[PDB]
Picture (cartoon, helix red, strand yellow):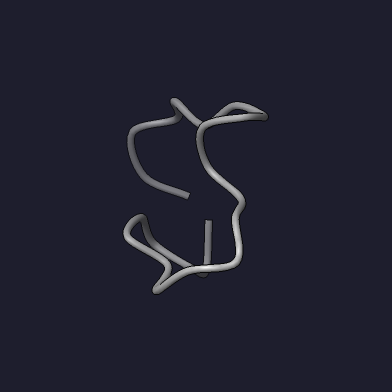
Length: 23
């Protein structure tokens, strides 16, 4: 993945994935 910076309660929800899905 590029630019690592994802976390729980702020990266996975039930809405239109805002962040990159491949990461």
